[PDB]
Length: 124
Length: 166
Image (cartoon, rainbow over all chains, first blue to last red; front, top):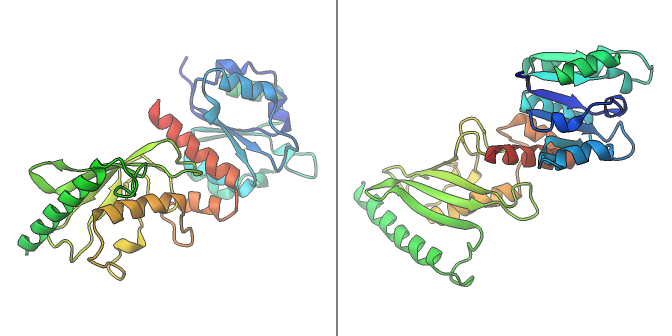
């Protein structure tokens, strides 16, 4: 019933997930968009699901990764969900996408390649 | 002292009342900059409160801000201590958790007793439209600016202010 505050990094794969976003717009989540690692703007549907409840301030676009990780720090949300497979040139996982620093400001970090786990976390 | 302090603040209080009561921008240059500046408790002239409106074309636009002013008994030889409410604002030069403000003009080196409370609160306002991030109190917001990530800068601030109201 009661969920933790999340900080979701919205690369290609996470935007692509089939999540009913209107269900979560109301909670304490923040969506950080890495525009540096997604060419266009963020999926129109995700934006619309948040605007619809006046929760459009929960979306943060980010020009630079250094900018994105600074946000993570300052927000200090409980969870931090991401998929490191999007930021590497070699398609696999590399724990070197998340600065060694982050363990200080955030309780739980999910870095997942598998769809179920990502949907499991963001939906509790 | 406290006798030379008190007669200053009484002079300032008159000037504050007069200027803020006008709705004409020649007599009131703080139109839309300073909404109110009064002493918290009429009887205690040493603590004061101001409400400012955030500067245009910044992430602080369209949100008011309450400021605490503490006047020392050795004022105006020494500066007043000025600070925000706790967990009220994110800024390079404001330590959000305490409210503390880094304003160069309030530093012992550069304080001129010519300045009064209105120039001070204005100097706070001026600071929101233009931050110095070489010496920041919020290292994280500082490093955002210091990377030219304006998308993040306006995003996190507008986020903070929006959740402040809810």
